[PDB]
Image (cartoon, coloured by chain):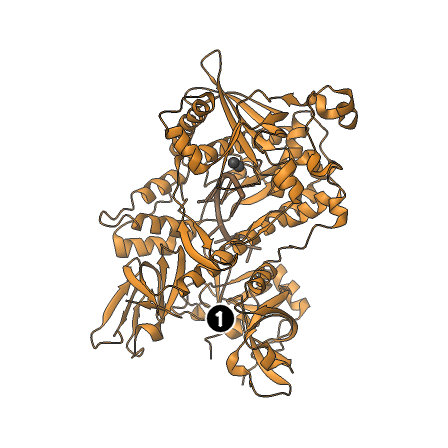
Amino acid sequence: DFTFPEYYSTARVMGGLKNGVLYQGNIQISEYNFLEGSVSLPRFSKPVLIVGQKNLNRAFNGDQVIVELLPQSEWKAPSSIVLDSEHFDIQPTAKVVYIQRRSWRQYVGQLAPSSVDPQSSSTQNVFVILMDKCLPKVRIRTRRAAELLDKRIVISIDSWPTTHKYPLGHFVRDLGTIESAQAETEALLLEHDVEYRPFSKKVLECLPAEGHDWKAPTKLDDPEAVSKDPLLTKRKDLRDKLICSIDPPGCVDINDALHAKKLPNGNWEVGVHIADVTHFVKPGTALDAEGAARGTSVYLVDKRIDMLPMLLGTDLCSLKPYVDRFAFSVIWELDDSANIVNVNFMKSVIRSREAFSYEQAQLRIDDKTQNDELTMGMRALLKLSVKLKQKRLEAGALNLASPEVKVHMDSETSDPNEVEIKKLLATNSLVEEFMLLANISVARKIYDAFPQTAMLRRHAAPPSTNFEILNEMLNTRKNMSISLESSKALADSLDRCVDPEDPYFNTLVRIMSTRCMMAAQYFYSGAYSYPDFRHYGLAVDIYTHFTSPIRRYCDVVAHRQLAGAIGYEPLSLTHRDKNKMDMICRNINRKHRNAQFAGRASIEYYVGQVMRNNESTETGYVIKVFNNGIVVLVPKFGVEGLIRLDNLTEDPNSAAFDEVEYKLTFVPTNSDKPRDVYVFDKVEVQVRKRKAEL
RNA sequence: AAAAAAAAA
Ligand SMILES: [Mg+2]
Ligand code: NA
């Protein structure tokens, strides 16, 4: 029996805060040990460790907490052990003395089977294991214990008194079975609070009266068309450009289309044409309000949760082929070296000639028998994109991009059959370079027009502390290093991290470097000074998101600001008010992050069940070593698995972790003879319910 | 918030 320390009185907290004795921060509990935590505070070169139950003082991941630094005698290094709630029962160091703002929402979990009596009718004290592996188990009291046994449940937490080792909560609702999929998708979206309800009648009431019969006007000065839409006479007719779009296979939500036309003077006319979402999505409407709140589209494996009604996303705003669409066009004159000669922005009417997938586009460009006007355009674009990318890389751009996973379904829409690691084609880079070009040109334009409230996106340099462990692993294990002299040194040394008799190693390190990045963040220009507009990863001075207004709210704002900048329409005073802008960025950074998390956890879920139906052996790479396990990346599946010590060894008493060598030594199960497993090792792995080292 | 860069979804 113990008692956590009582939180400091509210008056002690504000007195300590002011005297510089107490510090305030958001707690990040570690991704592998739930009884160990961190607070990042600009003072100290390193985040401050909070180690153990008492010191964490009933704090939940994400809590705004108040910490007190401990004496140097109590300073500790991070744990060499994996720990979640399910398996439970030197650096500057702090203790939690108070909880300022709590992150108790409704939480998804599953009953702990050993806390439940499956034959008892009466009310039981049972434990709930939360889906978030950062959190503690929660005691609930319920008469339905047996009926909730292998089910997906929502619980609410009520309290965690000083006197209790575990928080107390209650059952809220049932999602369904742990096998379901409907229940695991509802669970996933709750954990990341993505709104996925149908769009209200109020939202739908904003959509064009014509519905799917909406047509772009034939003549831009047609008196009828100009009466309903007076701004149409500022719209440029570009229905003469041989435009095309290049997207993933079978994609309905087409944001962008491109053209390239050789000019009379030797230069290039290049257009990037983007769905004109802000023509349909007006400020202060219920439709703008639902989209602003959603902030982003969320892509799950089996499911897309739209920011906007699909009448817009997949029909009227989509730059569909062979149909006249409105657009917002960025038009450059380019050198044959891809240097900007001039740039111009305009609302337009477009007619995409063809919608290609990446693969079809690639094969058409590489098809020596095809010599038509569209193919030559596409070929011109690929060429300009190569030069564009070359210049980005010379300027110090990072190329951290690795092959990602697409899961394929079987007999059912939620029953997964196989995992595809996506191969990059040159057309992927063709589109990316012009998206980048579009986004940079508009960011300069809107910051020009609105120096105080421009919708921008920055990316901080990583502290050296972000790369401290990875560089130590690379030195001790490989005699290699990642340089942080600059982003160019970072990119070049990363490129040179090569194992001759193992091409994957370089990709292993590239993916591991990506996790050492700072988060890129939307911001309004007035919040920072110009040198802090810096996008580190992209090595450009100013950046924004413009090219995807169907699926991201940042681009809706940027679009309005560009229409403001070119004198097409006045900018809504909403996007000229710093306080409203500041609240918008806060929200959309939150929606962006949540969507990345939800995305990844859907993939992890489906891939995990693909591998569960697979008996065979795979290649793995060790990306992490602990005293009681190893984390192994399996590239064929694109996912990590923990291999726990009870599976590596009988005699865990002799397992030995060498922290400076990143080496676990153990007597494997068959044997008498010890075995060394190091970070980075290529190993053989198989699933026999559990991942095992062959 | 020091809570994973970029592009298309
Ligand atoms: Mg596109
Ligand atoms: Na397309």
Q: Residues within 10 Å of mark 1 (few under 14, many from 20)?
A: many
Q: Chain of mark 1?
A: A
Residue A308 image offset from top left, x and y in percent:
65, 44
- The image quarter in which residue A491 lies: top left
Residue in the picture at 33% in, 40% down: A492
- The answer to whether residue A655 is above or below residue A535 is below
Q: Is residue A230 left or right of residue A162?
A: right
Per the image, label 1 sits on a secondary structure element best described as loop
The residue positioned farthest toward the front in the image shown: A411
Callout count: 1
- The answer to whether residue A297 is above or below residue A142 is above
Residue A258 image offset from top left, x and y in percent:
52, 28
Residue annotated with mark 1: A35
Residue in the picture at 28% in, 59% down: A681
- The answer to whether residue A198 is above or below residue A226 is below
Q: Quadrant of the C terminus of chain A?
A: bottom left
* Residue A83 visible in the shown view: yes
Q: Is residue A122 left or right of residue A463?
A: right
Q: Nearer the viewer, residue A570 or A10?
A: A570
The residue positioned farthest toward the left in the image shown: A673
Chain the render paints brown: B
- The picture's colour for chain A is orange
Residue in the picture at 60% in, 47% down: A296
- The image quarter in which residue A322 lies: top right
Q: Is residue A224 left or right of residue A113?
A: right
* Residue A526 visible in the shown view: no
Q: Quadrant of the N terminus of chain A?
A: bottom right
Q: Amino acid at mark 1?
A: Leu
Residue A574 image offset from top left, x and y in percent:
72, 39
Q: Nearer the viewer, residue A601 or A534?
A: A601
Residue A449 image offset from top left, x and y in percent:
64, 28
Q: Nearer the viewer, residue A102 or A682?
A: A682
